[PDB]
């Protein structure tokens, strides 16, 4: 059986395990050496109830743009981290006793529970694909639908309170995202992005020596322009502070930052003077920084990200939804808080973003092979091995989820992913009949990301316009056109 | 509940805002005083400011206060209706019974 | 009768359980399990199966109460004793005279 | 309304009076009243009761032994 | 009266009654949940994506 | 007897603050960490504490010398 | 022997009488589900509604089933079970008591452990000295030399935290005792009147006849009994849930207004700046 | 891994015949109590030092910086408004305990950081668990050795059980001596 | 399609607090009996009160 088949190679596996541990140690040393000087400090923050940490990718998932590492090497890093996770049953005899060998036997029974060393294959890509096709796709295919249902019922709420909890403008997008297994039509990622309307406006407060300022597209454009100009720091900081005071005046004319009038957040006013400390009409006591002149406004280097996720936040998800998201992403989930599973999910998210960056450095998706792209999509959890799609469809799927994960929101990511895991079984043998049309094929051009899409009104859905029909499409798609024709 | 709740709320607000008024009046310089330098080395202050911290530290502080002092408090409450009661003399052990040679 | 309708006499038998013997057999089963498994002291099995018993026994042997509980050693109803003066002494002397 | 341990605040940062106003007296009188007050009421009552029963505790068990002879 | 009794306050017979009742309830929960709602039939029947095509001419 | 929720503040009044993720620029503060031999000495002190507080079970004291 | 400590357990007819109560739940099929849905959606709005709803459904349907078996299926325990105090305190009241602590136990526990750090609640708390007092001193109040009395303080603050969870226990006990008393006293009084009337008619056999009728009196008494007990059960349920609302569920009122989002297709990130 | 199995029956014997407990047996039990109580504090210290050996600077500043230790009571806007809190005010809001000072020293210490989760927690729990279990095991061993070297009824019972005899046989053998020498059988 | 309804009672129990309620009820009732009714009624030293 597989027990004796794996026991036969158990002696030959320890050397490979230790070699992999050495590679992991070297790689983590290198990566942390880079991270400890280029990456900022994402402080730990606690949930609304202030008992457990909460995690978000915008702050904690950092991408080393400029990482001198091969994509296959990063795949090795992540896969060996998962192998370290899978090596945990070796501690059972060292905590239970000599009778703690039966857990090790159960571990050695199934090959999917095991690390890389017990596999006959050599290449990391073929090895990962074997593991997925043997164990991982099956485990994910039995969690996908029930996670989709939990996400639905998290939006719409329980016990017939949809008229109190759902929104009437995201309705058609909700239907297209969650009930496309009924129609068989493809989905547009922008309709999944429309789910963020349940949340508020995500803001970024830059902390200065006087007051916090809300970041805008204009200020960000100016800062990117100044950073691209490659000026001396005496001019760089001056231009940055000029843009900063300009934006400060702009928001002061707007009526202050958006955070002042949001439930759960707020900026305090000047402190009050109590009793005899009140000096006539001056009932307030301004801060020390009020003495500083406004022309000396300088950025402290500190930032505060506020997703304002009132319905989407991972804190309010629950004990079950987090565990099922980690099952669906093949992460550890048992016997841990939702904060620890949140961190595991954010680490996976960061890995996927770093992998996207390295692919873009290595020349995009088309430079990859077919098996490598299949394994990438399996890691992204948008493909099941019982599909056998084309290369253009795989590339379009990757582009879709890459743009969707660029927004840094796990809820919409899971809503997108779970749609590709709704498979049925027929009770009859003759039905379903053999189709007559060819397989579904697409291209990178069919994905509309460079254009905005308004939310369709309820019970008034609009047809899908191809990007090619837009004006100047041959100009906008020229990069993708050159990449595909080449 | 009682109708004196707004009265107690007024008195609580009085003492709280008067303490804050006192802190405003005395202003800065508290860190240079001897009281602060002793509170920095005082375990009561450490426990009291760790109670309000996040990460389950309120539960930790409350349970620690229970395990340490609240048991003696429960015993004290049980002994309040025992102090006034007639009790007999303590039958002190003669410490003679129990000794036995080994074999 | 109404009380007969408010009565439950549908019992079948009395289950008699020697909880002392059952506790002894439980401890013996725990010892047998720990010996057969040859489990160390740092195991969660050993901890769960030994520590609470040892803690409770150590507490029940460390307890040194100056006085016993409330309804066992004081606060008890007692008839007033006979006084050595007045009417009680006269009754005592009259009893001694009548008996002798 | 009229919640427990709750108090509203006006634009001047002052507590609004729910039943009784006590902000007319001077700060010196308020500090005199509140320097010894705490956020605790019933524990002092229980403590005074315990001190009364301690003042009036029984010592018969010592009389039988001869600590007062 | 009979029910006015401290013996009937912590009756072990009724505690066994409750125990057996809720163990059987726990056993039979997955059969109580087996009632069908016809809401997804409605969603399948009535959900109609926009089927019109684009025609620039 | 006892109070009510109508006579008290809510779980939204308490804990009213939602979550804000603070981030700080990297100036180089977590570099040049000293005390490279700290954890070795810590483990040595821990094992020393365990050795001084160790007590082997000596059943030979129960031997029937009498 | 010395080690043998023997305990006697009084065992009777439990198994076959408890099986048919669960087996009847497939026949009833939760007929009270709509009523409890309406009441729960009146009193609270959260994702954990379904949990507490299901719990209440189970409790209520068990009550109803036991009551109907007590009225109709008169054998053994089904007669006593509604006349007994243990059923009214533990088989109906305890479940309703622990239901919110099982659904929203996390929030209530955190709330209680925060209330042990007792402090004055300020609306629009834009004060700075309040924060310094809360961090440095731990509370708004003056905590000088309370460590001198900490032993009582702990437990008193614990009671101060659960005082607003205690009236729920009180109301549950009160209404359980009320239902027990109602059933017992009404049954006893009715049976007593019946026995006195039968004594009068046995001593006067001109009247020892079916003077009202064989079915008339029985139907009327059936209607009286069922109407009265239905009123009492509706009272016990409606009051239990209204007091659940007014005592425990007003803590969980967290209304979030809907704020429109604008930056849907673009999100600022750590990489946008750094 | 063998003393607790005898100490169970010995403790049952002591609980039953608690009248036969001496002062030296009482002191042995009190010393075992002292060791058990100190084992909790030792476990807490080991847990702290282990998690601190795997906590990053952000996880440490979560416990030092009052921005994070004030999240329950204070608005975040009071910390975003520059000049709201003074330097001395932030200093009085910082924790002063020995753990805070240890972490403050540990800022400048090289370590092996991990992501905040189950492994950073297990690296503290495992040393704490081993410390607690080993201290209690050695305390019970010391207790049993003291009882075996104690010339008393409980010492005789412990000795007779350490020979390898059954609990019932040992109880009978010791009660045969108690009835004769101690109780003075008729 | 996988369901804990038909494939795992453990995950079904874990995913539903309204299934934990009867178990906690049982535990509390048995603990109440253990604390109060055991020694006062069922023990041989305290069984004559039924007379
Ligand atoms: C055995 C396996 C152990 C391994 C750990 C268990 C699984 C991991 C886990 O539980 O996370 C820890 C959990 C984290 O929960 P979370 O994942 O973050 O979910 C929070 C979400 O926001 C919440 O999201 P959600 O809404 O989806 O989840 C809700 C869920 C959340 O609940 C849970 O978290 C349950 C988690 C399962 C725990 C397993 C317990 C199994 C027990 C058997 C060392 C400990 C020493 C101390 C021991 C003594 C306490 O349910 C509840 O809210 C109710 C919980 C309470 C149920 C029991 C209530 C009994 C009431 C009795 C009546 C009381 C009447 C008196 C009233 C007095 C007047 C007021 O934290 C802890 O409980 C403490 C951590 C350390 C100890 C854990 C184990 C013991 C305590 C439990
Ligand atoms: C405290 C917890 C703090 C950290 C929590 C994280 C954690 O513990 O992860 C466990 C972890 C759960 O899996 P995961 O981390 O979520 O990742 C799953 C993968 O993604 C793969 O996911 P998958 O979908 O492919 O599933 C893999 C499959 C296969 O999993 C395997 O790797 C092979 C199966 C290993 C079974 C080991 C359990 C043996 C139980 C004792 C049996 C009797 C022993 C002999 C007689 C004594 O999983 C299973 O079939 C069952 C796994 C769970 C078994 C129960 C483990 C008990 C953990 C102790 C804490 C919970 C109780 C409180 O268990 C494992 O999979 C590896 C074995 C862990 C050994 C840990 C040794 C320490 C045990 C302490 C005992 C405490 C007992 C206290 C109550 C008595
Ligand atoms: C009775 C009906 C069955 C009882 C099952 C209950 C399971 C308990 C449990 O697992 O706790 C973990 C569970 C949390 O675990 P988790 O981290 O969410 O992970 C779920 C398992 O890993 C998910 O399980 P899994 O997918 O990892 O499958 C493996 C598992 C499944 O296998 C089994 O557990 C049992 C095997 C036999 C059945 C197999 C049928 C197929 O076996 C194991 O190796 C670990 C189990 C130990 O705790 C709870 O949810 C709390 C519920 C229990 C407490 C409720 C209140 C109790 C009364 C309180 C009284 C005092 C109040 C005052
Ligand atoms: C038996 C006695 C044995 C004694 C053994 C002592 C020696 C053995 C171990 C030494 C201890 C080592 C230190 C340690 O373990 O720290 C663990 C733990 C974490 O320490 P930490 O690393 O400093 O945490 C920092 C941040 O939290 C880190 O944040 P994070 O994101 O990494 O994860 C945070 C997560 C912790 O993450 C985990 O630790 C995972 C735990 C699972 C793996 C095990 O959440 C917590 O912090 C837990 C705080 C507990 C309060 C929260 C509310 C719990 C509600 C429980 C359910 C509802 C209760 C019933 C409701 C009905 C009544 C109203 O510290 C604890 O607070 C332990 C508490 C355990 C008891 C909780 C029981 C709650 C239910 C009580 C019911 C009422 C009865 C009591 C009155
Ligand atoms: C003096 C008299 C006492 C004065 C008042 C208390 C002072 C302690 C204190 O609380 O101050 C605050 C202070 C807080 O420091 P911080 O800088 O403000 O906070 C820093 C971070 O925020 C901290 O952030 P972090 O999360 O990284 O820290 C981890 C957390 C710890 O990590 C954890 O998360 C674990 C949490 C454990 C929670 C407690 C266990 C709860 C278990 C569940 C309970 C369920 C309820 C059960 C009740 C029944 C329910 C029905 O730290 C703590 O919370 C400190 C815990 C202090 C240890 C308490 C251990 C109690 C064990 C219970 C048994 C006690 C037996 C009696 C001991 C002997 C008595 C004299 O605590 C300390 O720093 C002290 C720790 C060091 C203790 C060493 C003590 C000296 C021992 C010397 C060697 C042995 C004696 C040698 C002979 C000496 C001559 C006689
Ligand atoms: C010593 C006295 C003990 C005997 C009677 C106890 C009365 C306590 C008197 C203390 C007055 C302080 C305020 C107070 O206790 O509280 C006075 C209470 C109100 O307390 P609550 O608002 O907290 O319920 O008034 C009452 O209704 C009961 C006292 C009746 C007289
Ligand atoms: C094991 C049961 C032994 C036995 O025969 O016992 C049989 C008895 C039935 O005996 P009677 O019906 O004759 O009284 O049932 C029980 O004792 C089971 C009690 C269940 C409650 C405890 C759980
Ligand atoms: C217990 C030891 C605490 C030592 C201490 O500083 O104690 C500090 C506290 C006072 O602290 P505060 O003045 O800050 O309230 O002392 C006390 O409350 C009395 C403790 C008894 C002291 C012996 C008499």
Image (spheres, coloured by chain):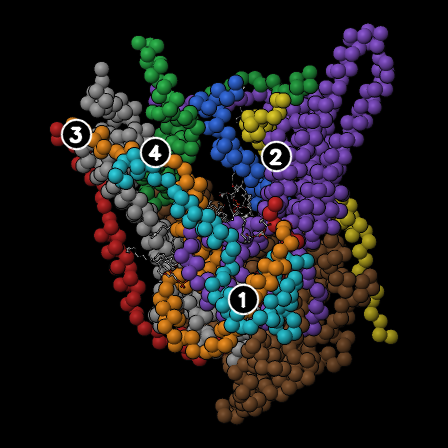
- Label disc, if present, on residue A294 of the rendered structure: none
Residue where numbered disc 2 is placed: G89
Q: Circle 3 sits on which residue?
A: B102
Compute the Cα span from label 1 to label 4: 49 Å
Chain with colour blue in the figure: I
Instruction: Name the one closer to the observer, E49 or G57.
Output: G57
Marks 3,2: beta carbons within 8 A: no
Provide the secondary structure element on which disc 3 rests: loop
The front one of A246 and G191 is G191
Residue visible at 30% across and 38% down in the picture: D62
Badge 4 element: loop
- CB contact under 8 Å: marks 3 and 1: no
- Give the letter of the chain under mark 3: B
Labels 3 and 4: the sequence-earlier one:
4
Chain D: colour as depicted: cyan
Task: Spot the orange chain and give its letter.
Answer: B
Front position among marks 3 and 4: 4
Q: Say the numbered circle drawn on residue B88.
A: 4
Mark earlier in primary sequence (1, 4): 1
Circle 2 residues within 10 Å: few <14, some 14–19, many ≥20: many
């Amino acid at each position: 059986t597989a027990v004796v088949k794996n026991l036969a190679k158990l002696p030959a596996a320890t050397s490979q395990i230790l070699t992999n541990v050495s590679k992991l140690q070297t790689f983590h040393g290198l990566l942390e050496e880079r991270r400890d000087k280029y990456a900022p400090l994402a402080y730990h923050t606690y949930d609304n109830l202030k008992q457990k940490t909460t995690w978000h990718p915008i702050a904690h998932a950092w991408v080393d743009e400029g990482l001198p590492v091969s994509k296959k090497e990063y795949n090795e890093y992540c896969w060996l981290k998962k192998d370290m996770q899978r090596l945990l049953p070796l501690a059972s005899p060292f905590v239970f006793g000599i009778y703690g060998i039966l857990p090790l036997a159960v571990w050695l029974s199934n090959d999917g529970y095991l690390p890389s060393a017990f596999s006959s294959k050599k290449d990391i890509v073929s090895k990962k694909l074997e593991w997925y096709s043997s164990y991982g796709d099956d485990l994910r295919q039995q969690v996908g639908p029930m996670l989709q249902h939990r996400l639905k019922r998290h939006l719409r709420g329980t016990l017939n309170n949809e008229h109190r909890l759902m929104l009437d403008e995201v309705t058609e997008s909700y239907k297209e995202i969650f009930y496309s297994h009924y129609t068989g039509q493809l989905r547009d990622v922008r309709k999944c992005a429309h789910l963020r309307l349940y949340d508020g406006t995500s803001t970024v407060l830059l902390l200065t020596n006087k007051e916090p300022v809300e970041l805008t597209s204009e200020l960000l454009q100016k800062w990117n322009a100044i950073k691209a100009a490659k000026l001396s720091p005496e001019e760089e900081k001056k231009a940055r502070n000029e843009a900063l005071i300009e934006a400060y005046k702009e928001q002061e004319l707007h009526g202050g930052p958006h955070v002042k009038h949001m439930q759960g957040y707020g900026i305090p006013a000047d402190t009050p003077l109590l009793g005899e400390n009140a000096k006539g009409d001056q009932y307030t006591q301004p801060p020390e920084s009020a003495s500083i002149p406004l022309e000396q406004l300088e950025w402290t280097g500190d930032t505060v990200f506020i997703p304002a996720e009132y319905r989407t936040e991972m804190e309010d998800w629950g004990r079950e939804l987090t565990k099922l998201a980690n099952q669906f992403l093949l992460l550890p989930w048992r016997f841990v808080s939702n904060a620890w599973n949140q961190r595991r999910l954010v680490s996976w998210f960061e890995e996927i973003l770093q992998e996207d960056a390295l692919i873009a450095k290595e020349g995009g998706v088309q430079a990859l092979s077919d098996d490598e792209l299949k394994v990438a999509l399996l890691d992204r959890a948008v493909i099941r091995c019982d599909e056998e799609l084309t290369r253009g469809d795989m590339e379009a799927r990757y582009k879709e989820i890459s743009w969707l994960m660029s927004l840094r929101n796990p809820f919409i990511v899971l809503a997108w992913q779970t749609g590709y895991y709704r498979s049925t079984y027929s009770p009859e043998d003759d039905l379903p009949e053999a189709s007559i049309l060819p397989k579904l094929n697409r291209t990178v051009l069919d994905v509309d990301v460079h254009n905005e899409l308004a939310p369709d009104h309820p019970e008034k859905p609009l047809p899908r316009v191809h990007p090619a029909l837009y004006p100047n499409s041959h100009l906008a798609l020229a990069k993708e056109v050159a990449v595909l024709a080449k | 509940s009682s109708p004196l709740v707004p009265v107690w709320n007024d008195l609580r607000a009085l003492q709280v805002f008067t303490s804050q008024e006192y802190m405003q009046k005395r202003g800065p310089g508290f860190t240079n005083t001897l009281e602060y330098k002793l509170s920095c080395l005082n375990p009561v202050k450490w426990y009291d400011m760790m109670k309000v911290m996040p990460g389950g530290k309120a539960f930790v502080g409350t349970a620690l206060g229970l395990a340490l002092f609240g048991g003696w408090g429960v015993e004290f409450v049980k002994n309040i209706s025992v102090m006034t009661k007639e009790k007999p003399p303590i039958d002190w052990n003669n410490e003679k019974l129990g000794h036995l040679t080994r074999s | 009768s109404p009380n007969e309708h408010l009565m439950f006499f549908d019992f079948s038998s009395w289950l008699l359980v020697d909880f002392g013997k059952r506790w002894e057999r439980w401890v013996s089963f725990k010892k047998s399990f720990l010996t057969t498994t040859r489990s160390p002291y740092w195991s969660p099995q050993f901890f769960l199966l030994t520590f609470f018993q040892l803690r409770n026994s150590n507490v029940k042997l460390c307890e040194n109460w100056n006085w016993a509980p409330k309804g066992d050693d004081f606060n008890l109803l007692h008839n007033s004793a006979a006084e050595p003066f007045g009417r009680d002494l006269k009754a005592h002397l009259e009893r001694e005279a009548g008996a002798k | 309304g009229e919640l427990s341990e709750y108090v509203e605040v006006n634009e001047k940062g002052m507590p609004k009076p729910q039943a009784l106003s006590l902000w007319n007296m001077p700060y010196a009188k308020r500090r005199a009243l509140t320097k010894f007050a705490r956020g605790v009421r019933w524990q002092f009552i229980v403590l005074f009761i315990a001190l009364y029963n301690f003042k009036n505790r029984d010592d018969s068990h010592l009389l039988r032994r001869g600590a007062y002879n | 009266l009979i029910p006015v009794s401290l013996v009937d306050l912590i009756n072990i017979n009724i505690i066994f009654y409750i125990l057996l009742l809720y163990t059987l309830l726990l056993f039979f929960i997955p059969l109580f949940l087996a009632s069908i709602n016809y809401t997804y039939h409605y969603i399948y029947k009535y959900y109609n994506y926009n089927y019109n095509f684009i025609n620039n001419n | 007897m006892g109070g009510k929720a109508s006579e008290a503040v809510t779980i939204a009044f308490r804990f009213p603050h939602r979550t804000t993720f603070l981030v700080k620029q990297n100036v180089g503060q977590k570099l040049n960490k000293g005390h490279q031999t700290f954890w070795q000495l810590v483990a040595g002190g821990w094992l020393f504490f365990l050795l001084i507080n160790r007590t082997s079970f000596k059943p030979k004291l129960a031997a029937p010398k009498v | 022997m010395l080690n043998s400590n023997i305990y006697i357990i009084i065992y009777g007819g439990i198994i076959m009488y408890s099986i048919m109560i669960i087996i009847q739940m497939f026949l009833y099929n939760f007929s009270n589900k709509i009523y409890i849905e309406v009441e729960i959606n009146k009193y609270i709005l959260s994702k954990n509604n379904i949990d507490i709803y299901w719990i209440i459904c189970n409790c209520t349907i068990i009550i109803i089933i036991t009551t109907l078996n007590h009225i109709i299926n008169k054998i053994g325990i089904y007669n006593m079970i509604e006349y007994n105090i243990c059923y009214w305190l533990i088989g109906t009241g305890l479940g309703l008591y622990i239901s919110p602590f099982i659904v929203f136990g996390y929030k209530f526990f955190v709330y209680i452990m925060d209330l042990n750090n007792y402090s004055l609640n300020i609306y629009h708390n834009n004060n700075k000295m309040n924060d310094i007092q809360q961090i440095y001193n731990g509370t708004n109040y003056n905590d000088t030399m309370i460590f001198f009395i900490k032993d009582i303080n702990n437990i008193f603050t614990i009671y101060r935290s659960i005082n607003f969870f205690m009236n729920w226990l009180y109301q549950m006990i009160y209404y359980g005792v009320r239902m027990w008393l109602v059933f017992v006293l009404h049954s006893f009084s009715l049976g007593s009147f019946g026995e006195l009337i039968t004594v009068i008619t046995d001593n006067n056999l001109i009247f020892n006849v079916f003077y009202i009728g064989l079915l008339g009196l029985g139907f009327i008494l059936y209607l009286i009994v069922i109407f009265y007990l239905g009123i009492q059960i509706y009272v016990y349920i409606s009051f239990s849930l209204s007091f659940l609302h007014s005592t425990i569920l007003l803590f969980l009122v967290n209304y979030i207004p809907h704020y429109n989002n604008k930056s849907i297709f673009n999100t600022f990130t750590n990489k946008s700046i750094y | 891994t063998h003393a607790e199995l005898h100490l169970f029956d010995l403790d049952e014997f002591m609980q039953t015949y608690k009248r036969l407990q001496t002062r030296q047996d009482w002191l042995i039990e009190n010393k075992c109590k002292k060791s058990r109580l100190f084992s909790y504090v030792a476990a807490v210290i080991a847990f702290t030092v282990g998690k601190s050996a795997t906590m990053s600077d952000e996880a440490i500043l979560a416990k030092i910086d009052p921005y994070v230790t004030s999240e329950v009571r204070v608005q975040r806007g009071a910390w975003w408004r520059s000049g709201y809190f003074t330097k001395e005010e932030v200093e009085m809001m910082t924790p002063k305990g020995p753990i805070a000072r240890y972490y403050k020293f540990l800022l400048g210490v090289r370590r092996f950081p991990l992501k905040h989760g189950a492994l950073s927690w297990a690296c503290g729990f495992v040393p704490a668990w081993l410390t607690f279990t080993s201290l209690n095991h050695w305390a019970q061993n010391r207790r049993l050795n003291r009882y075996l070297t104690q010339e008393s009824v409980f010492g005789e019972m412990a000795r007779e059980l350490v020979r390898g005899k059954t609990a019932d046989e040992a109880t009978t053998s010791v009660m045969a001596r108690v009835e004769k020498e101690i109780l003075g059988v008729h | 399609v996988y369901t804990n309804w038909q494939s795992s009672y453990t995950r079904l129990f874990v995913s539903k607090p309204w299934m934990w309620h009867p178990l906690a009820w049982m535990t509390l009732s048995v603990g109440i009996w253990w604390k109060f009714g055991k020694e006062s009624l069922c023990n041989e030293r305290s069984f004559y009160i039924h007379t």
